[PDB]
Image: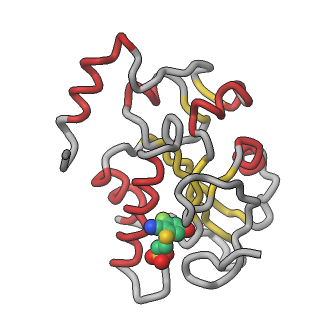
Amino acid sequence: HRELIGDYSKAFLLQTVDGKHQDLKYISPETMVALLTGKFSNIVDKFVIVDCRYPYEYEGGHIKTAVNLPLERDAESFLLKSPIAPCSLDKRVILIFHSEFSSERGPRMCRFIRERDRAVNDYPSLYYPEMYILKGGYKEFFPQHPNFCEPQDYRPMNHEAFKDELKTFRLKTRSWA
Ligand SMILES: N#Cc1c(F)cc(O)cc1SCCS(=O)(=O)O
């Protein structure tokens, strides 16, 4: 009972929960685990978990199999230089973006990739028609499913010991207010 995925080919596969960006689709930690455990494997050929946090955050504990792509230029290169395509036409590729709380950084990246994907395709085709945000980010995922994380820990962006690493990262970004 929702709208189609972004190339209007079919419905969203995963059950979604409410999130503050009302036009994006959010999933729970339980759904993320369903992907990781192959619950959807007959249909989902590939999925990419895009950890949008800074490298020190990712190094302090991330979801197994996640890729750390906090800079837009790096996310664009990884995802769109040579798009990640299912090995059967019957099957799907899904992207899941998250950040610490999935408040700002994850949603931002999700939108950016959609804008890029639209730009490089003939409307309405997309390389990544089906993208989700992990509701509550790493902060909510880790306490529920620690064995799906490595290392089994959680390093916040504003960790007191990583103030320098935060500044170092910010000076690599393409724009700030
Ligand atoms: N932006 C954005 C966006 C996205 F990243 C994933 C998604 O499921 C929906 C949206 S808002 C609609 C943008 S568009 O009409 O698909 O180009």
Q: Position of residue 173 (x, y in %)?
A: 22, 43
Image quadrant for the N terminus? bottom right
Q: Is residue 15 left or right of residue 123?
A: right
Where is residue 78 shown, x and y percent of the image?
39, 55
* Observer-nearest of 24 and 81: 24
Q: Outermost residue, top direction?
A: 161
Decide: is 10 above or below 155.
Answer: below
Residue 114 can be seen in this image:
yes
Q: Residue at x 52, y 50 (%)?
A: 97
Find residue 48 and report its horizontal and vertical position in percent: 56, 53
Q: Residue at x 25, y 32 (%)?
A: 169
In-image side of 83 versus 139 (left or right): left
Visible residue check, residue 85 = no
Q: Where is residue 147, by image quadrant?
A: top right
User: How far across and how far down the image is residue 56, in percent?
Assistant: 39, 25
**Location of residue 161 with respect to 58 vertically, above or below:** above
Q: Looking at the image, how many numbered discs can be counted on the residues?
A: 0
The answer to whether 174 appears left or right of 101 in the picture is left
Taking the spot 19% from the left edge, 46% from the top edge, the residue there is 177
Quadrant housing residue 88:
bottom right
The color scheme shown is: secondary structure
User: Which residue is pictured at 73% across the width and 30% down the height?
Assistant: 145
